[PDB]
Image (cartoon, rainbow, N blue to C red; front, side):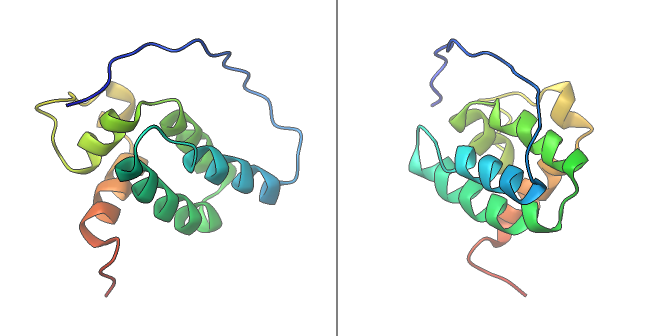
Length: 109
């Protein structure tokens, strides 16, 4: 249940690129993952939603790429017992999109 290991990262909030290349970047970092469970979840989610979403929504998605594998997976599966839901996701539409994705994934219509 979870992997609470803190990592060394530099939060460089800069965008000087084509918006199609930014979608490719965020979908790429979405397919860089610690576990295959969150990998399959965010790979299908990113490839689908980043096509329809504006850069503002993509920046909320950037905030999701800063989060840990198992934490993302528990909020999507509604296992808030193991990983409690933070403020940034408590009022977020993107979180609810990820939950509404999790129920479907391999089942459309």
